[PDB]
Image (cartoon, rainbow over all chains, first blue to last red; front, side, top):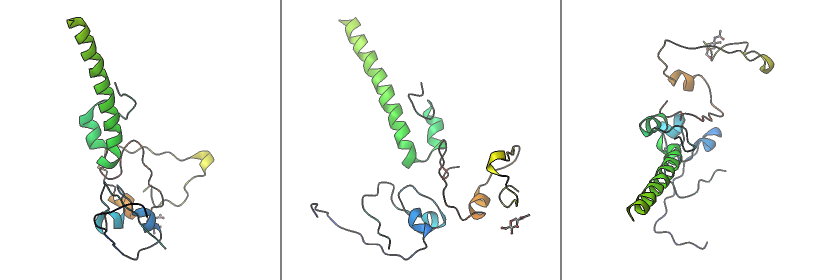
Amino acid sequence: NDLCFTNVYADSFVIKGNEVSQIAPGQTGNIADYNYKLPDDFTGCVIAW
Amino acid sequence: SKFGAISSVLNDILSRLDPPEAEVQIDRLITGRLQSLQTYVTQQLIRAA
Amino acid sequence: EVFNATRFASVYAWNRKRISNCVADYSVLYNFAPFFAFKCYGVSPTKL
Ligand SMILES: *[C@@H]1O[C@H](CO)[C@@H](O)[C@H](O)[C@H]1NC(C)=O
């Protein structure tokens, strides 16, 4: 709550359990390779509930 | 000299490792090589004086 | 022939196989296992 961001991207997608561990910069998998690849210089958070 | 990384040859390490894990080792190589170059240039300056 | 074996030997006697003189395409390796941990150290799985 102490920072000023230029713009924020909110990408929402429902996925399996292990795919939560799959999503991270510089990762791999059936989803991380052909469905959602995070940028290598990712600066943000991923939320999973 | 490997300088504490996987290998001492860049043209092999770039193809053996992807960027988001290879940048650390290539940074180790950069710091070692540039420290050696700093030593060389300082000694050359002393010899020139 | 090493990923759908049935009697992976116990840890105290770890079966070790030698693989040579073939072409390695690890797509079979990915699709033959619902991976839980792929921690590689000396080489990245991506450009493998
Ligand atoms: C080879 O893999 C298939 C696919 O999982 C499996 O059903 C089969 O049992 C395997 N072969 C043997 C001998 O277990």
